[PDB]
Image 1: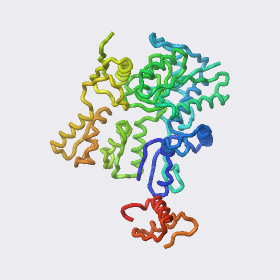
Image 2: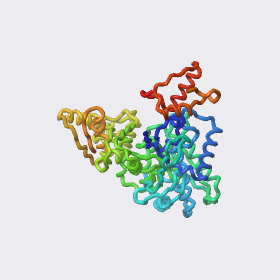
Image 3: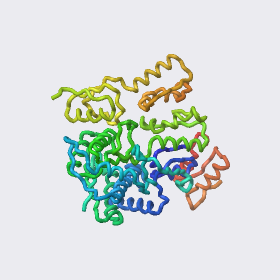
Image 4: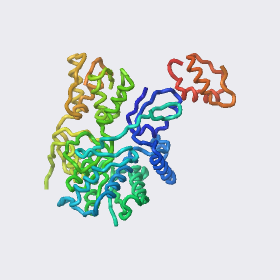
Length: 150
Length: 168
Length: 100
Length: 51
């Protein structure tokens, strides 16, 4: 019984291992059961196929990597915040004189207390730390029909 | 009407184009597709591609970006670089949005970063809860590097509380 | 116009000045033990703290000299967990009923 | 037993053989179907020290 705590197990070609009989529990951050999320990951795999592809740069079967999903969620998070914001301009800052942003803590709060359902499930933030606290880790397991959520 | 963000991406060479950068450009193009997300503003992006393991270059690009005008930075992959860019953004009060989890030296008191990667303590608690569900008795923990021991902290320390023998 | 820098005593504050000393080619002299950076391609830093791998080999050698059969590793921070790695892996090689 | 003639995937045969606990197996094959049945016996996970 193998148990991979990597959040990318789903993106692994497990057919040979599948026909063996291993209990092969893992993890999955992506709620690909959602129709919108499955359409987004299919659109991303379609966009990554019209480019000259990179096979054997890993053992992905043509899926979205977790780092790609989190970056997608990041740009959607700042987009949700800017949509919910006031007239948020942008000030050209410096580094030799670190003048603080006059929109700074306002827009950082409007980022942090903003919830959104992205490709990794719910995106919520406990505003005392900045870490991602409420999140659903789906459990996948390898059976004869592939990788199924248990 | 514009809103400009910035992204600092580490790449070894240009043959392996960054999937982080590709997802970044994919996400900003889908935001420019969707006109239900404040359509009067257009969200544009400013990329800076740096070499791998260069906190100094990451700092230079962050400085140049904040001199150009950036509303939010998406930092690099390496931990020292993303902590340096996080401290730059925390001093400058611009938000920093990182997607890679970092080594547990987070006691630097910051409130201008969000780490979309799940908490390495919560992943260990999930692994412990799943092993307590499966009722295993002998578990062979196999890691790859010290980040792995930090991420399996709770599972390895779990045996004194619950009856499980652990070989590491 | 400094000849060589003596940096601060925490990991995030020292990994910025180490990269500054690497890019400006002045000798950085670290004193506290820094968290293990995965590059190891920075060249212009020297460090006087003995590394946690050799400290862990020392505690494994001294446990094996004392012939303890079951120990109780107690840490207070993950830097310490990274350090005690040799002792934690030791049950596979030598008979030690470890417990963390 | 006899491996199936047309559908060269003998995975139901190997599954029944694994289910009824037959570890000492003699194959009478040609080398081509021997290599294909070695691939199929690897995919069934029956390449252990028991078999």
